Amino acid sequence: ADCNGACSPFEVPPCRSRDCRCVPIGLFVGFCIHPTG
């Protein structure tokens, strides 16, 4: 698994891959994802 699970802003990288992005939607949490590049 590359960029998945929960993502954090306080954290950086938010997941571990810069090509991936953190999607904070939970008013209290976000989630990591690794789209195709």
Image (cartoon, rainbow, N blue to C red):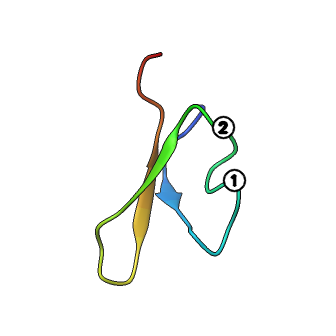
> Is label 2 in a helix, a strand or a loop?
loop
Which quadrant of the figure has residue 10? bottom right
User: In the picture, which quadrant includes the N terminus?
Assistant: top right
Q: Please determine whether, in this image, residue 1 is positioned above or below residue 33.
A: above
- Circle 2: residue type: Ser
Q: Is residue 10 above or below residue 16?
A: below
Residue 29: image location, x then y, percent: 41, 74
The answer to whether residue 4 is left or right of residue 10 is left
On the image, the x and y values in percent for residue 25 come to 29, 67
Q: Residues within 10 Å of mark 1 (few under 14, many from 20)?
A: some
Question: What residue would you read off at disc 1?
Answer: 13
- Give the number of the disc on residue 37: none
Circle 1: residue type? Pro
Q: Is residue 37 left or right of residue 23?
A: right
- Viewer can see residue 4: no
Q: Are marks 2 and 1 in contact (CB under 8 Å)?
A: yes
Q: Residue at x 41, y 66 (%)?
A: 30
Residue at the spot of label 2: 17
Residue 37 is situated, as x and y percent measured from the top left of the image, at 47, 16
User: Tag 1's secondary structure?
Assistant: loop
Q: Is 1 or 23 nearer to us in this picture?
A: 23
Q: Quadrant of residue 28?
A: bottom left
Is residue 22 among what the camera can see?
Answer: yes
Local packing at callout 2 (Cα closer than 10 Å; few below 14, some 14-19, many 20+) is some
From this view, report whether residue 4 is shown above or below residue 24.
above
Image point (68%, 67%), residue name: 11
- CA–CA distance between discs 2 and 1? 7 Å
Residue at 48% from the left image edge and 32% from the top image edge: 34
Residue in the picture at 42% in, 18% down = 36
The total number of labels drawn is 2
